[PDB]
Length: 220
Image 1 (spheres, helix red, strand yellow):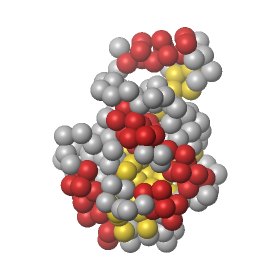
Image 2 (tube, helix red, strand yellow):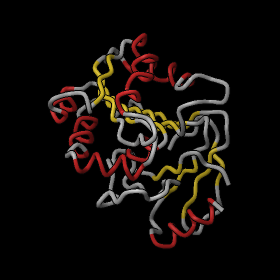
Image 3 (tube, helix red, strand yellow):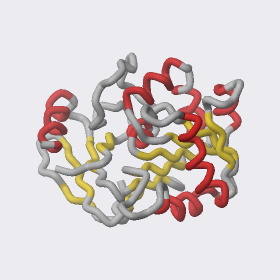
């Protein structure tokens, strides 16, 4: 499988998605057709959310279509070579994806070879559940289960308390591995390999285990 899971969209002083471009270009391998899932977005229209993405990705050979601008979203996902999931509120992203019947189809399509790119809420969505989002529960998603494509739980925008909250999760779900992924960092899964990247310190939390700092290049 091919996933690019970014903690966030924009480095300080840089353009929205700029640090992700080389990563995406490296991973596309000729793929062009993309559907953008805008549902995490709240304060900006989904229509407008779709354009910034197309803007920076079009030169990379990616044709981005908003999943809210197509007549048959299920078929759009089935035919897509790339699934892009933007940031925003994770609960709304999951609620809409589930209600619209797009959750399993997105997972199926990525399992069948499509490249998945998600940042912030979109990185959360790739995990087994959204139990590690920092977002407020503004809408009930009718289940916390998510795409279940990446086996570990990612806590994006990580900064430490946050560790205390993660430790409470580890009391109720002792089998989990939680990755505190700081802004600026990402996890790129490609050719049978999940690799950590970025200049900031990443942390991993497991039940009964001291926090472990992971270095860029660490393979999960």
